[PDB]
Length: 582
Ligand SMILES: CCCCCCCCCCCCCC(=O)O
Ligand SMILES: CCCCCCCCCCCCCC(=O)O
Ligand SMILES: CCCCCCCCCCCCCC(=O)O
Ligand SMILES: CCCCCCCCCCCCCC(=O)O
Ligand SMILES: CCCCCCCCCCCCCC(=O)O
Ligand SMILES: CCCCCCCCCCCCCC(=O)O
Ligand SMILES: CCCCCCCCCCCCCC(=O)O
Ligand SMILES: CCCCCCCCCCCCCC(=O)O
Image (cartoon, rainbow, N blue to C red; front, side):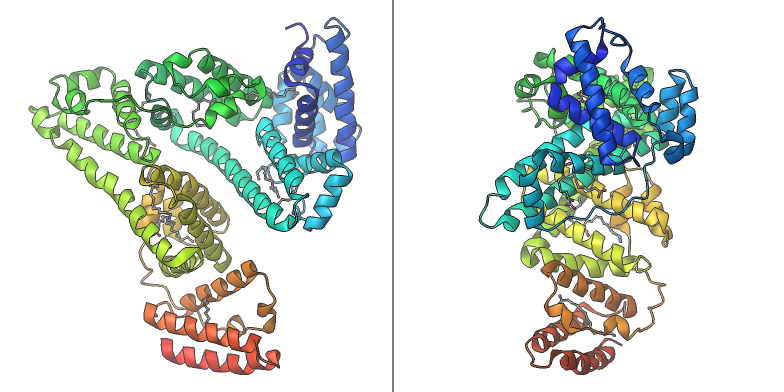
């Protein structure tokens, strides 16, 4: 186009345009105050409108990169506030845009964003809706400078809807606060999956990524022919490679190009895309990324004919090994939207190892005729774990399910900090509540997605304060083996019990007036410390103490002098437990 800035304004609309411009400037200029950014936005928006009136007007034919970088270099405090970043302005394009990209700070050392009180939030929302939401858009964007800007805007719009509904409710906090909690976790999770995709691309390479994509696209689009899936894998690997590099415009163009291709070829891909493909450009690729799986074709034959029984298996494999393995994966995956992606990848690795071994024998057909037998236990291991865990969950409920997990994992890796053990155990209990309520055919993909978030959060905490070689092994393995590795951890036989600390087991009356969440965390913290100190305690012995503890808190919180109960009765509880455990 003649004026790229005009074309974006016409397509996005003024409101969306202004929000994305704010996000982009805040992700580059993460230390500038909100008011400086509003000013930049308004100046960009009035310039764009001149181009919309006349694509021939001055500087309207410049590229978006040129115009955006020129504008960053007009910021008066650029050297004073960002130092080295200001040297990027001495560069010509495209060197200049690359230089700005390298100086984004993914950990900018800003204070934590505090969630104010419900009445305070709703009153600001009422008083000035636009400034309220845009100031938070700025606060979030500047702390997460690689988060894809359109998706940030998608969250903002759901926040607007939560405040609009809940600030009119009779019980405002009961309406609003679980919505805020859901949006925060979903947002944190989306950021985790973006960073994990990019890190895994770098370490394990393009082929491993393409394998994942084949499985993932074949479950989503089971009616597509392999050649169409395989072209989609190629395009999607380009999109993720460019987006991981971090330039917003290039990432957005690649995503938009792929969505347009999909929507122009729906008959070859899926019957579920009509609604997404009617949406504006801004929303299209995100919508497609979240489409439900297509219904699979009926009466698909077994894989045995093409992959086990054919006389030609080794010949077809040897002439194009990755293509044949891709076809096996495509056929296996389109048939099993109830499997995790990593499960499908385990099966393809197993099939590959067998063909490597068996196509070297004089009778390969005899050698690999049983290969589908090897898949059965790989498939069953995660199915059985889900059954067991969801059963335990319905029998205990989330809290006591969390506690069962807390004791198990403390004993396996008692060197982990107590905060992390509590947090990871709680989040794992949340996975059970979320995914156990799905029918069986959707439980494994649910578990894979949310476990990938929780286990990454663990590996991230641990990578920075490492304490256990066995965790570091599970966190550095292939992502295909990550969960089985964690599932294979055993009780630490060589741990030296932690030395008793009286204060760790001293409880005060503030526990009666704490939040339910903080009371839970308080008790789960002490349960972890209890297992760290007496790791060889039986479940019977632990339950006895947990029951003594429960009577101890309920009694003292109803007693006239509470402070004295907790200290005197408390001393009794400790002395008795110390005798009943070891
Ligand atoms: C990227 C979304 C921006 C839209 C505005 C966010 C909503 C305002 C409240 C945010 C307060 C912190 C949230 C939380 O801690 O749960
Ligand atoms: C957290 C990843 C990007 C944000 C996605 C929007 C929804 C979450 C809003 C609340 C997150 C707080 C951000 C922070 O405190 O750093
Ligand atoms: C169609 C192009 C992709 C070909 C993929 C071949 C898949 C078979 C081997 C899978 C190996 C597992 C991936 C990984 O190591 O993480
Ligand atoms: C940065 C200057 C403002 C205009 C361009 C903002 C970036 C384009 C985002 C909208 C396109 C989304 C495409 C997609 O994700 O499928
Ligand atoms: C880069 C994400 C947006 C690209 C456009 C959607 C193409 C089909 C995606 C199918 C699901 C893949 C999930 C993913 O990797 O985001
Ligand atoms: C602090 C981290 C300690 C180790 C965490 C282990 C994570 C296990 C992931 C799979 C859990 C499936 C349910 C189960 O069998 O417990
Ligand atoms: C905390 C337990 C959550 C529900 C039960 C999860 C059991 C393990 C799931 C295994 C499937 C995830 C992906 C994989 O390893 O194949
Ligand atoms: C040797 C130290 C003994 C300390 C005795 C008190 C132990 C407190 C464990 C608390 C477990 C709370 C579980 C619950 O009922 O929610």
